[PDB]
Image (cartoon, rainbow, N blue to C red; front, side, top):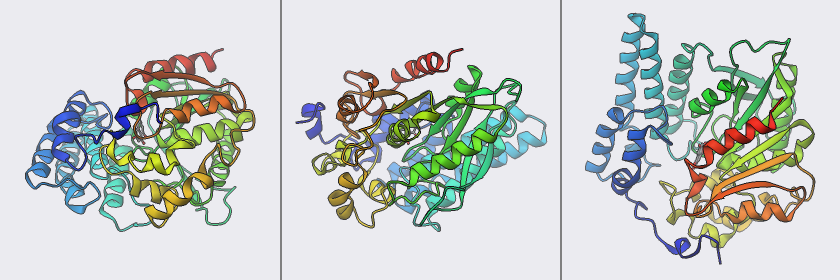
Length: 398
Ligand SMILES: O=C1C(O)=CC(=O)c2c(O)cc(O)cc21
């Protein structure tokens, strides 16, 4: 039925086993300091995962999992304080970024927007504080701006916290192009250090905003219209920033962010030069058949509970029954209008969202651009990263 093929029916060996996850995948990912351990260090995680495996802790959503990381995070914060006192700004920055990753992994896979007393919310708050302290020491610092949500309606919150980083010499005389990153289910505004490095390196500004139903996004998750209002507020603020050129602006949707990159490519086409949708869902990811086996694939932990909450549902049952007709960009007709240039990047063997959710967009509206990696799972890393920057360079060219 699915392009994923036989692999669709495979129960992946890490399912309900943190031991297998660490020993097969995450240990190596952590060593290489690649996603989701980017900015991180194996020195910090080896003892934590040894602990979790020794206690047979497998459920990431449990407090037993989360609170096993916080003592390490504390030790790194004190080491950073000791580094700062001695005027070692580089080491302090590194140690605080390392602390941020310990917090990050601790609140995987999802910070529950509806539970503000949750230990995963606490960890996320500590992460943001540690990250902003770390990036404050950078030559080009990451700055937080609380953008007033002027376009808010109904159940929308008042404040849009975004991260902004501008390249050396960004001036109103010659305002710089903008890459607006839309983050995902387990990646929020502090989880994009290397992306901001690569954007500034090519002389562009990096802007990072969370998506509806995650982190500190004020958009009503249960209202499919809410992201349209969110970007109206975000883009209005960037219009007003003298050193940022909204005439040369691309959006970069990361995993769950991909949906909102595709949506914005249509809704805000006359305000964007381009959009990248990186491992996106838009339709078939909400098919009950697909949702029946999504928890059995490459995502480190159970995803269906987090997805239900992110889509503004009170139960997984209601989410499965309703989500597709309500949120599908195909079903709702968002795809049946022109779009700005839209690059679609994924692994063909994505078991989190189907490759069909890229291929479907070629049957609607404007021509779409795509590169799909045969054999690779969700996101198609690391192959899909170089081509992203090549495409940005072409779209934002002089
Ligand atoms: O694969 C994911 C993923 O599964 C969830 C994400 O949110 C994410 C992200 O924010 C950035 C990434 O580079 C990758 C991911």
